[PDB]
Length: 215
Length: 215
Length: 194
Figure 1 (tube, rainbow over the protein chains, first blue to last red):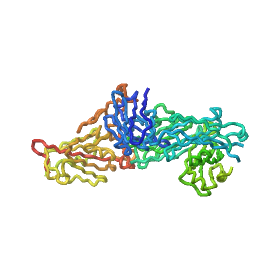
Figure 2: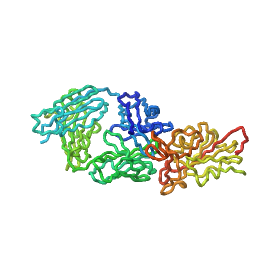
Figure 3: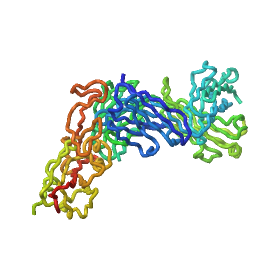
Figure 4: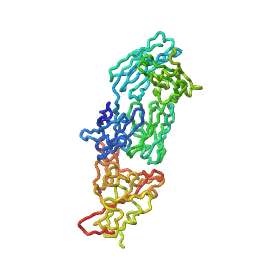
C-alpha cells in the first residue's frame, strides 16, 4: 500500500523552470523527513534536498538559490520547484522518506526524468555499416544526430533477432545522440538475404528503413 | 565531510557463491550511520540494510552487513540469480549525505575473445561533410577491453566515444562499439584507419584496419 | 570573594543529554568570566549582544547557564538564527539572544573504546521548539495514519536516539560539551556583577 508516485519531469531549455510532484500514500509527508535524490545518466546517486517534519529545509550546494522544496499537507504531496535549470541538472529524480539512523531511505518514488538541453528535437540520419568484403559476417546501422531519447531499432521488421546488439546511445558534444545497431549473420547469406534496419524516433515522427548491403 | 569508497568496482560471481562487498569511510563514523541499497537498471534503489547490520523487512536473510569506524561490509551468503545488480552504501544522519560509487555484481563465465570488425564511413554520410568510423567488439568476456584508434599510425585521442551492452541474457558476454568522428576534410587527409583491440582472451592485440578509398 | 558557581557548571563530572539540557540559575554572586578557558582541544567562545572582552565590567539581573553534550558537526546549531535537528528539536536559542556560547571537544571524557551510548538526542518531533523550550517526552512518534499505541514498528519510532561516542571516530562525530550563558535585564536589582 505504501508508495510515492512522482510526476512533473520533462524536457526543458536551460534557464527554464519545472515543478516535480511526489504524491504519498501510507506515510504522512508533513510528519517525515522527505528528501529528493537524483541520478544522472550513467552515474551514481546525489542527494538534492530535504524538508524536516518541523519545516526546516536543506539543499545541496550545487542547487542553492535555484531549487525549493515544499509540501502541501492537505494533498499529502511533496514538491520540488526547479528554476534556472542547467544542463548538469539532467537526471532521474526520486523522492524518498528518510528515517536516518532509525531506518534508511526505506520508501522511494518510481522516479521522473528531467532533461535540460538547448538542442532542437531532430530525427536521426541512418547510415549503413556495410559487411566487409574480406564464416560469420557483421553488419549494422549507425543512427546519428537525433534528440531527444529514445530511439527504437528492429531488423527485417522483427524477423531477425538472433545476434543483434543495439548499443546504448552516446551523447555527442553537439548535444545530439548517436548509437549503432549490429548483427552477425552467415557470410554465405550476404549475396542473397536482404538486411533492413527499421529505426523509429517518435518525438520527430521519424520512421526510417535502411537497406544494408555489401559494398 | 565524509567520503565513502566502495570496493571492488565490479565483481564477477556465480550462483551459490559467498560474495562480500566493502564500503570504506574516510574518517570514522557510528555503525548506526550506514545503509546499503540495491539498484537494477531502470529501477529505483531499494533499501537492504540500515545501521550497518539491521536487515530491512522483507529482504532475504542471505543478506547481511557488518562494520564500524571506517570499514563496512555487505555479504550475500549464497548468491541467487536475482542478486545480480549494483550496490551502493550511504551515510545516514547527515545533510548532505555521502554515497559510495557503487559495486556491480556480475555473472562469471569462461573467457571469450572478441570478434573484431571495422566499418568505414558510408558514402552517404560523406556527402554531408562528416565521417564516422566504427569498431565493433562482439561477444567477449570479461568486460575489460582496450580499443585504440590509429590513423596513419598516429594514436587518436579525444575524438572517439564508446558504449557497452549489458551482459547477454543467454551467453553472459559483452559487446562494445566505438565511434571515431572526423570532418570529411580530415578523413580525406589520411589513408590507414585502424582499430587495435586488447583483451585477456587474445594472445596479442588484434588490429582490424582498412585503407581509405580501396574496396 | 563570593564567586559564582561557574565551577560546578563548566567542570561538572557529568553533563546532560541535549534533549534534557540542564539549566542552572546564577544570582547573588561575583562572576569572573576569565576562568572560563580550560585548555580544551577545540575551545569556542562566542557572544551576542555583548562584548566578550568587557564581560567583567557588566552587571545583570540574573544569569542562566544551560549545559549539554552534542556532536562536533552540531556545535554550529547553537547560535541565534540556526536550524537543524538540534536547534529545531533539542535546544533552541532566540533570534535576539543576549549571552555567550562556550563549547569544547570532550573526546577524552565522553568517548570510550566499545562506545558510550549514554548521551541522547531527539530525532523525531512534529514541530520546532520555542526558544528555551525543553521537551523530555518519550511517546512513540507516529509518522503515518495508523496509531502507534505505545509500540514501535513501521511508521512508529522511538523519538530519542543515542549518540555513539568512540575515540577513533572523526572530529565531526566526537562529543562536545556546551555551556550557554544568558544575561537577563529587568527593572530589578542586579545580582551578577563582575
